[PDB]
Length: 67
Image (tube, rainbow, N blue to C red):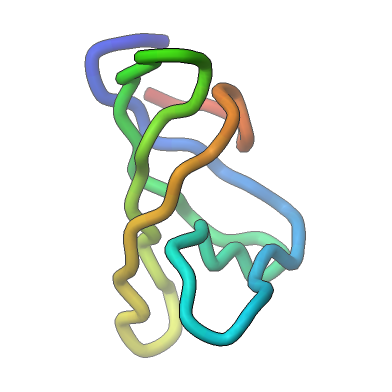
């Protein structure tokens, strides 16, 4: 599950005011890649509602990778 992967994450992940985080809204799609320069990767959110597209950093395998 490397070289770009899309993950399905079920959680409500959105904190702080202004921040870069995977805005997971309990059953949402995340389009991520495998960077791992220390342990965290960067990924984008694929929103299935309006188009909430934001980038966030996550500590490796966050959602269920469907590639």
